[PDB]
Structure formats: structure tokens, C-alpha cells
Image 1 (tube, each protein chain N blue to C red):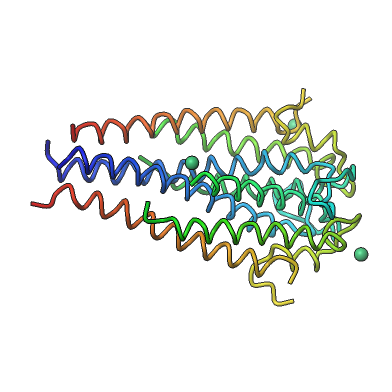
Image 2 (cartoon, rainbow over the protein chains, first blue to last red):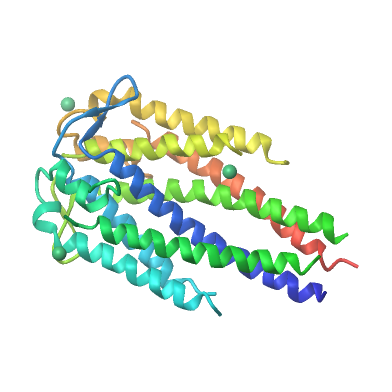
Length: 158
Length: 157
Ligand SMILES: [Cl-]
Ligand SMILES: [Cl-]
Ligand SMILES: [Cl-]
């Protein structure tokens, strides 16, 4: 086993995987935001109902979406190139769908129903959530491939 | 001894990944803070729609409790994980304790920024957010050092 070269493959694969994990976590944060649709912080630490004031919550989801795109615009690794480009495209289609639906998602008093169509995966139509789901799938594929590359480099140490 | 070093690399990678996930959740709160008082515009910019921040803050709060849960699930890092976990609880509790300004209809931009906008020159949570950020940076640095040092062992003679 050429330990110098295996060392470099491990380092590079870890660096890709770290960047992918950061993007996956940012996607997870949008799922958390979706739990706050139509909600407020109560004194008892629960979320209480306060329907139909979701505009700045959705602006937060949008800002996170553009950060995801910026990370994917810079990230690279052989057989990851296509998966990264695909994820970057999906991330742009998500942001574009939100912007295109500004007349429902970017007004005073954005309704719970419209916010759910943008970012709540459990929503049953699409104002962004289908693009969010495709983005999640694209990142899962990228993660699986990045993890397999790291696992293969570590295995060469036998 | 490559079997022992491989284990150290895979375990250190796994810890580092878990730490980076938490740091990225904290990053998302910093991005939420950019949306205080804002709405999505047709041209892709954020436009002003002031003083409707309660559900945005409920989102930050939800993320903050997830941070604590992930830290609860995490060698050589015990003290730094415990510090980060405590800081994360203190941030969530500060938000909840400020419900009278952060959990009402029409939360103002000013009060939202005192909760989650770092370096806000105008405390309703930001100081706790900043302490949490520093505690996760210290944990991240330690986890990175443990991975880097394990990898460096591979080529030692
Ligand atoms: Cl559309
Ligand atoms: Cl974990
Ligand atoms: Cl008030």
C-alpha cells in the first residue's frame, strides 16, 4: 500500500464529504423551518399557533437556499462531478421556484398553506417543495458516492 | 500499525462530520438573521417587510433545539462537547425566556436582531448565539486536529 498516496486520497475524500455534509445540514435546517410555519415561541418553550405571517420565515429559507447553491458552485471532487452539477442545478430550481411564486410567498401575510407548498415535505400544488425534495435526493446520491470513495480509500490500508 | 490507525481515522472522520453538521445548523441561523424584516422579491433579492419576525424566530428556535439534540449524541472531546451542549441549551432558553418580545404578533426587526443577529450593535439571545458559535469552533478545531494527526501517522517511519 502506497501510504503517502492513500493518505492524500483519504484527506481529499474527507474534505469533499465534509462539504457535502454541510450542505445536507443546511437542507435539514429548511425542514426545521417548515415546522415553524404558522408558529410562534411560547413562554412554556413550545411552538404556539399564529397562522399566516410566514413571509420572513420563507425569506430565511430562500437565503439558506442561495447559500447551498454557493457551496455547490465551488465544490468539486472523477465520478462526483456529474452529481455535484446535478445538485447545483436542483438547488437553483428550488430558489427559482420560490422567487417565481413571490405573489404568494413574498407578501405581507404569507399563509400557512402557501408556505407549506414551498417548504413542508409532508405537504400533499408545488410552490417549491417538490424542488426541495429533488434537491434532497440529489444530495443523498452525492453523499452516498462521497462516502463510498472515502470508505474505499480507508480500506486500501487493509 | 495500520489497523489501529485506520480505526482512528474512521472514528475521527465520523466525529468531525457530526460536529460539522452542528456548525452548519448554526450557520443556517446566521442566514435566517439576514432575512429579519424581509420578504422574497421577484428579482431574487430580499425586500423590506418590517416587523413580522415571529415565525422566523420560531424557526431559529426549532433549529436551536436540534443543535442540542445532535450534541447530546456525541474521546478527547468530552469537555468541549459538554461546553457546547450547555451553550446550546442557554441559547434556546434565552429565546424562550424572551417570548414577550420574540413570540408575539408582529415581532419587530430590532428585537429579532437582538436575538439572532451576531455583532448587533443595538441582549435577547445574540450573546448566547455567539458563545455557542465559539464553543463549536473550538470543538471543530479539536476534531479536525484529531483527524489530521491520525492521518499524519500513516506515513511515519
Ligand atoms: Cl411557478
Ligand atoms: Cl452522531
Ligand atoms: Cl410588543
